[PDB]
Image (cartoon, rainbow over all chains, first blue to last red; front, side):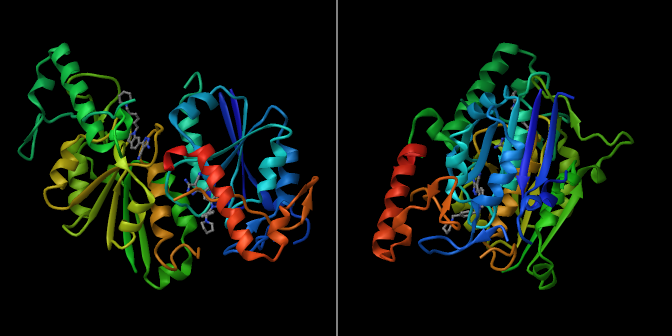
Length: 201
Length: 216
Ligand SMILES: N#Cc1c(-c2ccc3ccn(Cc4ccc(CN5CCCCC5)cc4)c3c2)n[nH]c1N
Ligand SMILES: N#Cc1c(-c2ccc3ccn(Cc4ccc(CN5CCCCC5)cc4)c3c2)n[nH]c1N
């Protein structure tokens, strides 16, 4: 059983019994009627003010909440992270936009609850929303009650456009197939992700 | 400058957010067009089957090459860059995003179940450029979330399309100068801009050492 609350200024993006997922429009906690301002010390782009975030998260979080903050400067979100989070009761995902969220939101929250700044990969997005969907998919499929690269998979027909299924897969020989697949996985891994086997990227 | 993106999926609804993210101005200026196609349009049977049991046995199902073959034959040309999300792909990185941002036609083939019969990509690669890629070291249910990430990372590099304008970036601060007892670091208000740049550099170095020591 898990509850996930996503907090965003772009709730429209997210519209698509063991688990519930709620999307909250951060603008509902605004004081006047602008969440962003210019960065201290200068620099391009705008920064989300901590004030609106503080009120929102106050209402939504408890001290047992795991606060997840997507950021391109975060710790790596990996399958190990996903296993770790799959047994949590309550995740709140704070989605930023502009050039991100004032650092004091995460620093303050970390005095009241567990906080995790994470990145889903080494590319730049426009905000936390797409990252939130990745994190949610990766975690929810591991919730109770739901190393190497995988080799190639095949199905019918056995011959297609003159291209044949590797004959070993039609042999019915379990041990030869397990061997052949173990081989394919290791060959794909060394070619595409040599770092996984301890070699230079 | 301008890009056509075709996405093929059995869940075209999952692609609603990319349409939600596209500004009307960029569409009307003909800078971008994103079409989403239901794979089942190309099925052959009354049950609209897209999957079948794996040769060699195993759990899960494999997506049928004949259905994918027809769909891609229709949508792709020899000038297409065919992108295939997969948990066994080459890493998709910012370098990848930069390279693809200058393409004229991207087609993203989103798999489900255990993935797509390998002959589909192998066949396609004999007449177009094909890229099997993974967006990170975690496991998803299919290619659709990866296509959202890929499309966003690529399109924000195409000038004027999404509306937007090595170490990890350090922390940022804005108003108010004091909040819940935490002050913005005084150096940022010192007006000494060489010292500010040095302070930011050192924050970046510390954060990188702590969060991503591999980058060093
Ligand atoms: N997870 C994850 C992510 C994200 C992600 C997550 C959350 C937010 C909230 C806002 N943005 C956009 C953004 C983009 C660039 C920069 C750095 N800039 C570089 C120099 C000029 C100024 C700042 C900051 C903020 C976000 C991006 N991107 N990539 C991932 N794997
Ligand atoms: N990009 C990207 C991705 C994807 C991604 C991309 C495309 C598809 C199409 C289907 N799936 C789901 C799936 C999940 C697991 C497995 C491995 N199996 C499980 C155990 C038995 C052996 C085989 C295969 C297929 C996809 C996942 N995941 N993570 C990324 N970074």
